[PDB]
Length: 97
Length: 275
Length: 9
Image 1 (cartoon, each protein chain N blue to C red):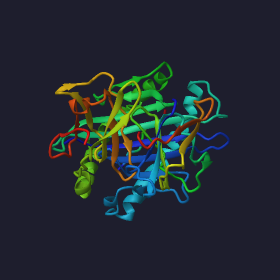
Image 2 (tube, rainbow over the protein chains, first blue to last red):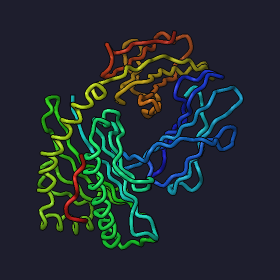
Image 3 (cartoon, each protein chain N blue to C red):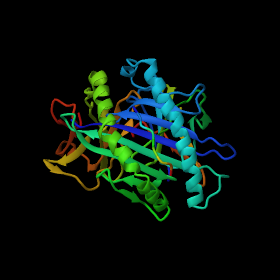
Image 4 (cartoon, chains in turn brown, purple, red):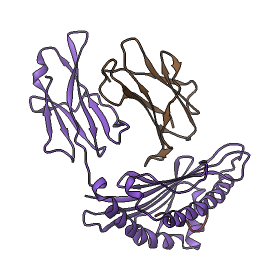
């Protein structure tokens, strides 16, 4: 089962206003996954991970988040490495979505 | 409304070790209330809801013992399917269980629930009758037949209709304020100018609980079922959810398009437009 | 409060 990712802020984005960035990874099997959050293509240290939970359709889900302060220049992405994919997936944050 | 208790048990086999990792997660009203993870430093059943603290350290002992027996149920169950499906222990394998019950508004038993999955695909299910079994493929027949000779269903029907019901009545009592609580969505429309004299109108809904919400877009009372982009209900991380709905609409015609939001915790359906 | 599965797979 192939992972589905959403990269989104916890509250409406306001440049300079402190926030939390979430990386919602779902619909994956087996549970072994590797999630990385990036700031300007560089691995963000201090990333929190939710405990391994699964859904009615047996697929697994996890929520990774990091404290971050939005700005015009700083781009944020999320890289996922799963056994079901050939190459790692990257989803870039879009404040409008 | 309806009420439920579920236990989401998982055993992942680790190659080059006799013991699999075993995780048990308990949910009351689709909300994690208890958890167990064998990987943790000092593994035991831990409280996941604050109203779970009002439980004696001897309840946790009773439960932790149960997790210890399950670890062995799973380890043996994993070994056997490895044989049924002619597999190698050089690789990891997944056995999953979902069991519990559902209750009406009157706290009365609606249904019992017990399902198993191997490698994340159905393996065996206990039919709503709590008597018969459904095997997913040929291999699940070794287990269906095994469980009919031993009368395993009887053991489960007993708990699912008895103790499961009892315990949830207790959990719904001890946590009611938290469990009967709802959070109202907080809507707004965002304007996205684009090419070909077109525009994206994205109606957001934020910080709401429970997860079920209905967002619909409407052209002067008429619904736009077709070409209305959505997003899967995502957790905000604060225990509340987010979701949005977009529609490509031509410029100036902004006020023709209306957005409606429906949710249990609302003093009425939300109705809103751009500005 | 969880149960214990009876017969193995």
